Image 1 (cartoon, rainbow over the protein chains, first blue to last red):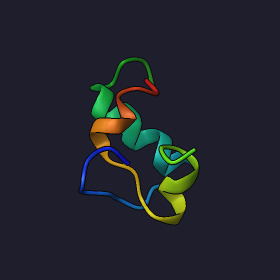
Image 2 (cartoon, helix red, strand yellow):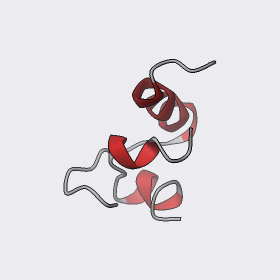
Image 3 (cartoon, rainbow over the protein chains, first blue to last red):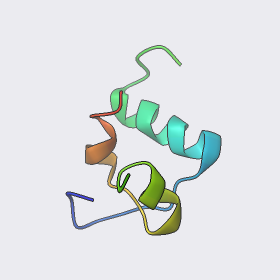
Length: 27
Length: 21
């Protein structure tokens, strides 16, 4: 919660969003 | 924590997510 904006992420969706931001590192 | 745990409840910033990956 560093940035003002926030999105509801749960389960695989949460992890996918992380990887999405990561730029498709290896998922 | 606030990044993972609180993300489902309140919400986590995509920028923050970078730390996990």
